[PDB]
Image 1 (tube, rainbow over the protein chains, first blue to last red):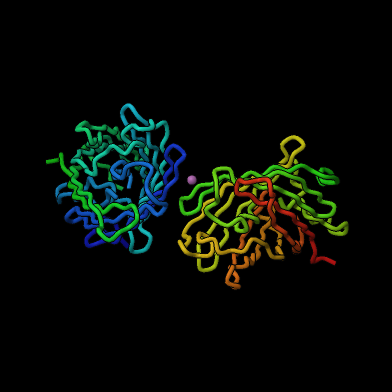
Image 2 (tube, rainbow over the protein chains, first blue to last red):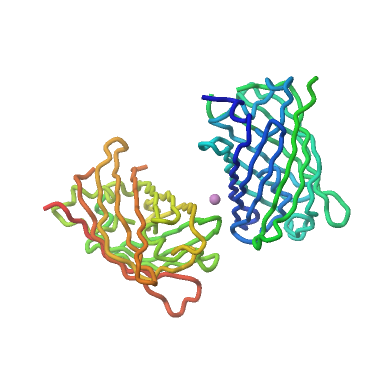
Length: 224
Length: 218
Ligand code: NI
């Protein structure tokens, strides 16, 4: 008995990520809350497998766009919420310029009250002591524009954008994202528009394990 | 079909798995003699020390080598599906701990019997009996209850493995098994297993001796 109606209030979030980069395996679990009426996430991620083989920032995009704030005049362009509760599949290919690639497949859906993002990630061809495996990325995340277009053919959407990762030496590591979402059930197909993102990364001062506290604001725009 | 097991047969076993995101690969080699129901295998953990105890991997490391007494040959699904082979799927629920999901192909490649497995382990406790390595290095005797699954033209199986824990308690692991051929009346397999070491092999390893015999039909 619902739809976008599942997001009128504060929703508990659970994220799990199975990761495989250059034969190094890891697992991340995140917990927190989202509030789509204001577009806010507040999450804590733990690398349960011990210290990560890649930098935390490289995982941020891949770790619930259903918590974007879609302004009242854009509600009919909100694919992510309309797929709920059965949810959607989110697939990406992430190209790190002059370095390796991530391929991800994710199921975002309601499991009871909770919104759950379960992810498989596989990364290949990363250079040793490149920015990623060498851990040369600053513990930062930049603002971006996620460009969304409809994919009528598969009853879903496509997304394109370039993530910018600050490197320690003052340079910038680019990560080209190509994104597909399709429904798991049986949705709104949007006119072209974008998401505007902002993200803070910090730590829990009493947490011994490798981890990431994340706060994020995202609003939809580009339609008048 | 059955004719492929009237003498000593070489075995190769390969397990690609990860448990709570901890990866590991295991290779096993040796022999089975299905007329007496005997397995003799050596398993190597390439990739280093295993994140889980060797005993938890036993069941999911070739039941076609069970001894099926003459009066029960009609009920041997395992052997009949050869050389084509079969697919073995399980879910193993460790009581008060995590779960394994496994998929395996058991088939003849040339003259050798091959068991190739995939394994996902989820939701294990960090200082539970598994991830904390609190299981004794041995292995109890069991009854594997087999039934017919006409719908998938194969069999199901259920049983409960008992793992001895160092403090003297018992870690139970509930097995659920499906086999499909890429059929018998109700019966069970009687198992016994000894595990040991090879003194000249450093790599985390398991040598396994095992005798299995089918019963439950007079
Ligand atoms: Ni995997």
